[PDB]
Length: 87
Length: 87
Length: 142
Length: 143
Image (tube, rainbow over all chains, first blue to last red; front, side):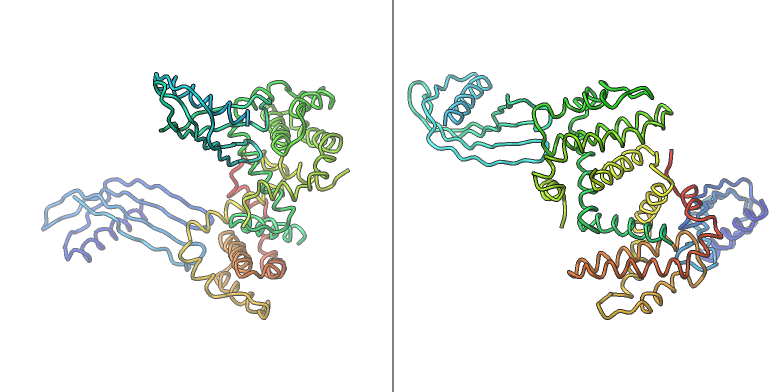
């Protein structure tokens, strides 16, 4: 619930960086996770509904964030990726 | 030779059954045979040229007849099928 | 170490088999007989059901009862197709045994199959070029 | 009598049981899990695996040291079950490449190299990580 908030912050911050936008993260409304962890890869997909301000006005957005580590050819490093971000 | 005659006679009978026709077998004019087989099934494939009477007039027909044998459970009594019959 | 050697050989044998190569002639026979069993069970689903239904193995089943039912495959003579049917028959009896929590019977069925091969099939196999000939006639090898 | 016929009976029964999710033996279960893992690895990592296989083409001249040096790359960050599967797949690729070049004699040498590398570099990690039985429970498709 704390680490969900960091991924939601990342989704807003990643959306703003990518679209030259100034949405302002307020909070996580709800979050779902699905996971596939094998001997080859760690993969969690997060579906976040968040509240953010667009020019001061609070609105609801859904973001899809993927977190992956390749256990074969990868580093210690995880990799966060924004897949989708819409109102 | 008599086995070739039987298959030619079967080809005419099966054509007449399938097409409500009355062709009358006269004789086999040429026969080619190939074999396809696995450890389970034998196919002997006959390309027959035969003479038959259509309203009493002798004409040439090409028939393709397959003789199939199940090598596991089958008896000596093989399975004939008519695949093609054309003038 | 010897287990580590056995894993290496099994894995390499499998990887060679996937490309149509073989570790050894024995590996090629094992792969051909595995494939032939699968093909048999596909082509003869209904007739094979009729054969397996004639013997429900229990702890009290005697070899002679297995031998009498297997003889039905070979009443018209031995051929490679009927030997494959015989291997598939044995495999189905093992699967059926484990399904019924009668695991005790898998070792017995293996012993019966080796007895039946020795007594009834091996003379024919040896005078027909051995398992090497089976691989020539059935194997999908490069 | 015939030891070859006994081996074919055991192999065929092991196969039929495995198709239904049963195992002839714990060793048969380890072999089946490694076969399945190698298949999954080659499907998922086709592109990255091609970058690994391209680094070594074995000839009669190639020393164990050249094999060891490339496999050592795989395990630079440590040993895990996925990298062990990759190692097996790498050896499999080297054996197929050898037979493709009409050099099947190299298959026995690669099998020896792999067994040497396993016992030298990987067996200590396998044993302290619960051995191959741990690999099966984790990864195996079993009834």
